[PDB]
Each structure stands twice: as structure tokens, then as C-alpha cells.
Image 1 (spheres, each protein chain N blue to C red):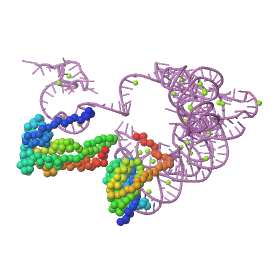
Image 2 (tube, protein in one colour; image 1 turned 60 degrees about the vertical axis):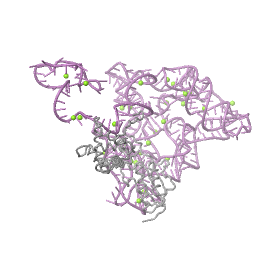
Image 3 (tube, helix red, strand yellow; image 1 turned 90 degrees about the vertical axis):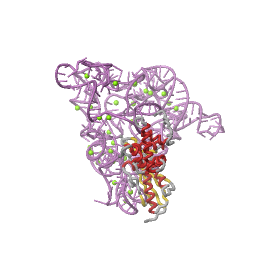
Image 4 (cartoon, chains in turn purple, yellow, brown; image 1 turned 135 degrees about the vertical axis):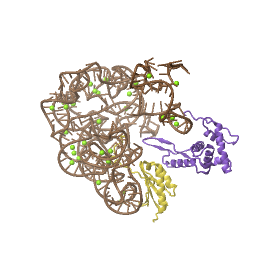
Length: 152
Length: 117
RNA sequence: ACUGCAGGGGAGACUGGAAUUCCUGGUGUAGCGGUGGAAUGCGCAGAUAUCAGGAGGAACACCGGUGGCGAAGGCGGGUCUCUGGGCAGUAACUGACGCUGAGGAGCGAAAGCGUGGGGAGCGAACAGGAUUAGAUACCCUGGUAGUCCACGCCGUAAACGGUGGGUACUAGGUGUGGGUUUCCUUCCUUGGGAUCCGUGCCGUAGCUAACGCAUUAAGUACCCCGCCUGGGGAGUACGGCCGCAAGGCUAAAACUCAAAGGAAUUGACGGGGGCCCGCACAAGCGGCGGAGCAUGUGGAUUAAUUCGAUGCAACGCGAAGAA
Ligand SMILES: [Mg+2]
Ligand SMILES: [Mg+2]
Ligand SMILES: [Mg+2]
Ligand SMILES: [Mg+2]
Ligand SMILES: [Mg+2]
Ligand SMILES: [Mg+2]
Ligand SMILES: [Mg+2]
Ligand SMILES: [Mg+2]
Ligand SMILES: [Mg+2]
Ligand SMILES: [Mg+2]
Ligand SMILES: [Mg+2]
Ligand SMILES: [Mg+2]
Ligand SMILES: [Mg+2]
Ligand SMILES: [Mg+2]
Ligand SMILES: [Mg+2]
Ligand SMILES: [Mg+2]
Ligand SMILES: [Mg+2]
Ligand SMILES: [Mg+2]
Ligand SMILES: [Mg+2]
Ligand SMILES: [Mg+2]
Ligand SMILES: [Mg+2]
Ligand SMILES: [Mg+2]
Ligand SMILES: [Mg+2]
Ligand SMILES: [Mg+2]
Ligand SMILES: [Mg+2]
Ligand SMILES: [Mg+2]
Ligand SMILES: [Mg+2]
Ligand SMILES: [Mg+2]
Ligand SMILES: [Mg+2]
Ligand SMILES: [Mg+2]
């Protein structure tokens, strides 16, 4: 708003996985107030990923988010008779939020049966750097880099 | 297939383009790479990014043809002057003295009518 | 009259530099130009760019200003020739020879007209592109007369200080320009003081409807000339004078209406300036508009579909219960 910033609400660390990250994904996939259901889906996906790989699910998630972390956005502006996109830098928190939203959205509309295996496959693809979120990040990066001339 | 260790650099920075040509001290052009010569078209040719990349193209062509140092003559009320200068400096070329050679008519030819946009 | 002073006052002749364009040649390759975005356009048959040389017309950066000059319009690249006016000083000379001026005469921005020349750049008309519903415009690409010179014509401008010419008087304060004058005369200061001619601003009285004027009056008086009697019709008609023409000057009436107008105040508005704010913008979350059902509305039908409500702020409203 016009009257300065608004502090962001804090989060708690999950007893099962002591990191704010897992709570962040639960919050992002939470819909209709079913926090327990979101936790169940994320735990099933993480257990599936651990079953398929062997390494720690939080480490796989960290690899995935580091791979899908973007650098610049393409926020647009209009001055006169035309509108053009302006590539600007992104803060780490905003980049993490955008990548998590992209991952969740692409896992929601995948061609599988349940979100356990859907999110397991999505996080594994993001960890290996070949998934839908990675493709979206590459597209955003290149289409923003194509507008480097208008960098005011 | 020439060798001109010393030469001259001319930058013409206007409101619609930016031309960077590199000549020998006698003024014979060796390279002339421009904002339009590099990938650009429309009004983007007058952008500082376009001017600086055209300077990069001109500098690399001069390096290929065998030029190590050039003096710079600039003219025109363009915004790519300093960016082109910096690119020519830190793209493998030395600029030395910087001089402005913008023509100054002593009240000669009548200018066109003012814009009524 | 004599001695000094400043000046883009004016006319003629010669001449200089910058810049644009064009021509020729060299270097050189794929773009150049243009806009808010583009396209028309130019180049690839060698363009833009760079260098050197040449041709040509126009206008004279810096000085340059709030300044100077001129009756007004207007006036600065330089040099020379001819010429106008003004200011200061002495009071040298004449002795009211002064002021205004109906008609009349001359001068008079730009645009335009005639004759010959010239034409770099700009640029009405015109053409293409672009915007838009349309775009006979604003923007872009071009481009003719014209802008320039010589001699004539035209005599019109918001030709304005929106203030006719001349004179006398009516506190001051503060800049600038041209002189002169003693003193402080070295306090070097070219400052201050006195006077004359101007040019700005602020300010006393006075005037004014107010805004404002205020020694450069719109104050206090005199002399002369010009002009007005509500707004349109109309600065138009007819007649007349001038003009190659365009048109200029003198200049009405019928009819129509009861206002047209000048200052200042409040409010409102603005695609005016400054600030701030709102799920208002922005980041996201969940919906409508697509399908079926319920309710209200419009229209149609009928015996009524009793009636009111109609933007946001009416539409599951009045109606928190129609067999
Ligand atoms: Mg003459
Ligand atoms: Mg020519
Ligand atoms: Mg050539
Ligand atoms: Mg050339
Ligand atoms: Mg006598
Ligand atoms: Mg007289
Ligand atoms: Mg008379
Ligand atoms: Mg004329
Ligand atoms: Mg003529
Ligand atoms: Mg002629
Ligand atoms: Mg046309
Ligand atoms: Mg034009
Ligand atoms: Mg033109
Ligand atoms: Mg004609
Ligand atoms: Mg005459
Ligand atoms: Mg005048
Ligand atoms: Mg009078
Ligand atoms: Mg008088
Ligand atoms: Mg008087
Ligand atoms: Mg004075
Ligand atoms: Mg005053
Ligand atoms: Mg009066
Ligand atoms: Mg008449
Ligand atoms: Mg007549
Ligand atoms: Mg008002
Ligand atoms: Mg938003
Ligand atoms: Mg819906
Ligand atoms: Mg619908
Ligand atoms: Mg009803
Ligand atoms: Mg309701």
C-alpha cells in the first residue's frame, strides 16, 4: 500500500521435517482449509520421491528449488503509444514463491491419477532440471532477456 | 588483410540511430558497424544498448582488421555517446583523447518548422 | 553658432568564416532516414558514414543585454565612400521667427502583383504514408509558387504603451546609458556629491468601477487635431476615388433583440502545477458471464398476471412465508 510495507506472517517448523520449506509447500497446496489433507499429499509425494531416489526428500527439494530458481521477471509498463516489457531483478523470497507456485500449478494439471504421485514426479523432474517448472523458468528467462534494451 | 596500428573512430549518435565507424588517421573507413547493422530495427536503434553493442561490433571488426588504438570523434545529441565510449574502451581498444566535433552553424541554413504534435 | 560625445540611423560598393545541400574521387558494405509506433522514401546498379577538392544560394553564432539607435515600420559578419538625426558644454548670434494642424503630401512589418535574374535550406498548394468511424489536419516522406536580388505596384497588421502632439507644476527609493561639473582627489574610487538628456522597477499624494497609473501619469491645467453615442445586420450594400489584379478608402438602410460588454468574488470544471489517500492500481486467492435449478425484472399472452420501485444508491427490493 501507500503507507509503507506490511510485515509477512511467520511460519512454524514441521516436527517431521524441521524446515520452513515443507510448511511453505503445504501452505501453497492448501485449498478449502484442509491443512491436514495438504500435509498428507505432500508427505505421500515426499515418501514416493524418497522411495524412488534414496536421498533425503528435503535435499531433493532443495536441489529442485535451486534448479528452478529464476533470476529476472518481465513486468510490463506502458508509456506512450505502445506497451513493452521491462526486465527487472527478483528478490530471493519472491523468486522462491514464484517457483513454488509454478511447480504446484504444473503438478495440478499433469496426466496422472492422484496428487501424491503427481507431486512426487513434479519434484523429481524439478530436481533433475527437466520438468514443466524448469521449462517455464527457461521461457521466462529468455523472453525477459529478449527485452534487455528497455531496462529503465 | 591490412594493418593499421593507429586510426580514428567516429561515433554519430542521433535520436534515431548510432553509427560507429573506424578509419585510419587519413579517414579511410576500415569498419562501420552500426546499431542497424547489429540485430535491431525501428526505434530501438537509438537505445543505449543498441549503441553499445554496435560499438562492440565495430571494436571486434577493428581488432580483426589489425587496429590497436584509435582516437574518438563524437557528434550528435544522442544518448549512446558515453555507453559507446565505455564499450570501445573495455572491448579491447584504447580511446585516448575524447573530442566533440559536432557541427556548429554560425546562423546559416534555416531549420525546419517546429513540431505541432 | 562653436567645441566635444554615443550609436545594429540609412544607402552604395568590395570582401570573410561556420554550417546545410550538391558534384568528383578515395575508404567501405547492407543498411539509412523517420516516429509514441510505423510506413511511404533512399541504397544495394554501391547508400548512411569518413576523407580531400570544388560549385552554389541564404543567414551572420560568440559579442548579445533588462543595452543602443530611429517619427513609426525597423536596425549588428568585416572594410571603405556618401549622408541623416540626437545629446552635452559656451552663450557666441537673431529676436516670438512658437504649438497644433481640416484637407493634402511623404514614409510605412509580413503576405501578394508586374518585368528580368537567382534558388542552398525552408516551405502554402499538391502527392504518398500514418492516426482515426471519417482525417480534405495535427505526425512522417517529398515537393511548386514564395522566401533572395534589381526597378516598380499594393498601403494593409494585436502597425500595442490597446494610452495623439506641446508646455508648467506635483514626495521619495533603487538599476542602466551619454555627457558635464567642483568637492571628498587619491578616500584609485574611477567610487560618492551636483546638473542635463533618456531608459526599467518599486513606491507619496491624487485619479479610477476595479485592475491599475503614479515625474516616462491614466494627477493637477491650458492650446490644437482625431474619434463614440446599445448589440447584430456591417466596416457590408449602392454611389464615388485609387489599383494590372487582389483589393484599399469614404460609407448606409430596412429588419431583428433587450441585451451585448468591462473589472472583481464565490463555486465548479481541466487530458494545468504541488502533495496525500482508497482491493483503487499492482502480487495472488476464490467467482460470474458457458449448462441445469430457485427468485426478482423487461417484453408477450390472458381474467388479473393488483401495485410501486429503474444506474452505481431498483432487480432473494417493498414481500421476516401468495391454497
Ligand atoms: Mg540595393
Ligand atoms: Mg544543387
Ligand atoms: Mg563515395
Ligand atoms: Mg559523403
Ligand atoms: Mg540683439
Ligand atoms: Mg506639426
Ligand atoms: Mg491632414
Ligand atoms: Mg515581402
Ligand atoms: Mg516577384
Ligand atoms: Mg520570376
Ligand atoms: Mg496524399
Ligand atoms: Mg511537412
Ligand atoms: Mg522538406
Ligand atoms: Mg500567383
Ligand atoms: Mg508607395
Ligand atoms: Mg511593431
Ligand atoms: Mg486626450
Ligand atoms: Mg501629453
Ligand atoms: Mg506630455
Ligand atoms: Mg534614473
Ligand atoms: Mg509601480
Ligand atoms: Mg480610464
Ligand atoms: Mg469596403
Ligand atoms: Mg462599389
Ligand atoms: Mg470561480
Ligand atoms: Mg492487481
Ligand atoms: Mg461462472
Ligand atoms: Mg455463463
Ligand atoms: Mg413488475
Ligand atoms: Mg438480499
